[PDB]
Image (cartoon, helix red, strand yellow):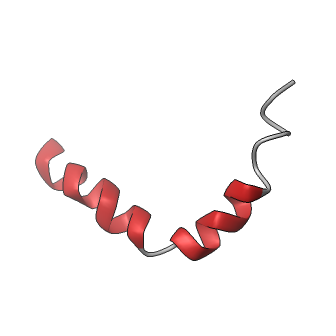
């Protein structure tokens, strides 16, 4: 009752964000180590 509402912009955005996110979480994944 809120999730299914999300996606869309996300499922889509991720498409345009399928480059930043990585480098993003990477900035942490590299520190998480």
Residue 20 occupies quadrant: bottom left
Could you tell me residue 12's position as x and y percent? 72, 66
Residue 23 occupies quadrant: bottom left
Residue 6 occupies quadrant: top right
Instruction: Give 29 or 17, whichever is nearer the viewer.
Output: 17
Residue 33 visible in the snapshot: no
Q: Quadrant of the N terminus?
A: top right
Q: Is residue 26 above or below residue 7?
A: below
The residue under the point 84% across, 39% down is 5
Q: Relative to residue 22, is residue 11 drawn left or right?
A: right
Could you tell me residue 18's position as x and y percent? 52, 73
Residue 23 visible in the snapshot: yes
The residue under the point 58% across, 75% down is 16
Q: Relative to residue 32, is residue 7 drawn left or right?
A: right
Q: Relative to residue 13, is residue 9 drawn left or right?
A: right
Q: Is residue 9 above or below residue 3?
A: below
Could you tell me residue 33's position as x and y percent? 13, 46
Could you tell me residue 17's position as x and y percent? 52, 69
Q: Relative to residue 27, is residue 2 drawn left or right?
A: right
Q: Is residue 6 above or below residue 25?
A: above
The residue under the point 26% across, 60% down is 26
Residue furthest top in the image: 1
The residue under the point 22% across, 49% down is 28
- Looking at the image, how many numbered discs can be counted on the residues? 0
Q: Is residue 29 above or below residue 26?
A: above
């Amino acid at each position: 009752d809120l999730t299914x509402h999300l996606l869309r912009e996300v499922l889509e955005l991720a498409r345009a964000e399928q480059l930043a996110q990585e480098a993003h979480k990477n900035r942490k994944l590299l520190e998480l180590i």
